[PDB]
Image (cartoon, coloured by chain):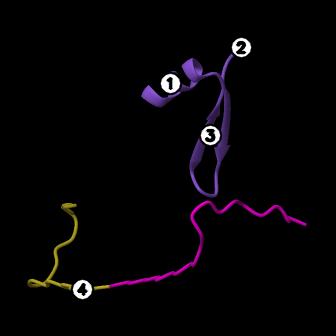
Chain colours: A yellow, B purple
Amino acid sequence: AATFNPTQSFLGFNIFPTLTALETQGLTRRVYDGNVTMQSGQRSLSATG
Amino acid sequence: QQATLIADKRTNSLIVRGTPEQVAQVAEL
């Protein structure tokens, strides 16, 4: 975005810089280990309240 | 008629009950 002004004139050179830098990492683990003991011909249970 | 079939879920047993000809048909299936 450049402009020109024919009515004024700046003194010297100015640079006015600005820097920004960012880095990031993440790591989520979630583990489950379930046992159930049961029988061969096991049926469901109907309680359900 | 047709042969009687009895299925047991606990033991996974199939029981066929009928005339000897109707029972040999299920036995080959």
**Nearer to me, A16 or A5:** A16
A26 left or right, relative to B10: left
Q: Is residue B7 magenta?
A: no
Q: Disc 1 and disc 2: Cα gap in Å?
A: 15 Å
Q: Which residues are magenta?
A: A27-49
Alpha-carbon span between mark 3 and mark 4:
70 Å
Outermost residue on the front side: it is B20
Q: Label 1 marks which chain's residue?
A: B
Task: Indicate the amino acid at tag 3.
Answer: Ile
Residue B29 visible in the current orientation = no
Q: Secondary structure at mark 1?
A: helix
Separation of marks 2 and 4 at Cα, in angstroms: 80 Å
The residue positioned 38% from the left and 84% from the top of the image is A29
Residue linked to disc 2? B1
Mark 2–mark 4 CB contact (< 8 Å): no
Predominant SS along the magenta part: loop
Residue drawn at (21%, 71%) of the image: A8
* Circle number at residue A4: none
**Tag 4, which chain?**
A
- Local crowd at mark 3 within 10 Å, few (<14), some, or many (≥20)? few
Identify residue type, mark 4. Glu
Relative horizontal placement of residue B10, taking residue A49 as reference (left or right): left
